[PDB]
Amino acid sequence: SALGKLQDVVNQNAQALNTLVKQLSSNFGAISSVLNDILSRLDKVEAEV
Amino acid sequence: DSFVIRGDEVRQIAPGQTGNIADYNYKLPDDFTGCVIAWNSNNLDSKVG
Amino acid sequence: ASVYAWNRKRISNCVADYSVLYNSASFSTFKCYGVSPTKLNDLCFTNVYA
Image (cartoon, rainbow over all chains, first blue to last red):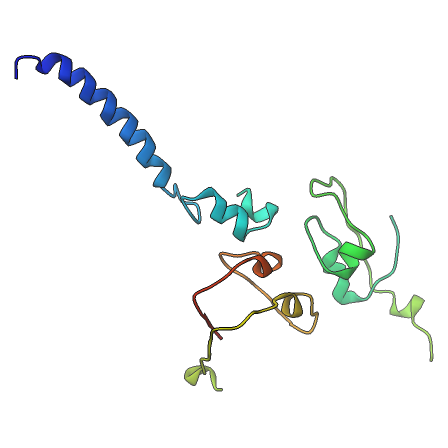
């Protein structure tokens, strides 16, 4: 428990990268979170939107 | 660019359109800058027989 | 069918060809949602309901 200051620096940088990776699963209002769905389902005029 | 087509096919004269008129007769650029102007010509172009 | 009493067929266990559909001018409208009609021939589906 005494090294909590250094373990906190390891833990904060993991929370930051895990949040950044998990944000790839978000839609952001698109048809899918997976970019290959959009490109395999829609033609360019609708895909690019 | 000037030509005659049937009224149904006039919809194919726009960017990103597909079908035998767009794909095998007259194809626009996807990013075309221009105007598409059309008029019915049954009184000019149709004939008996 | 009547529109209040719409009739559903499950399509399954078969190969499609949607170009037979989307190339035909016979259809007074052909509107697709979540897919481009010209892209239908590349896909597969669990079932279709007509």
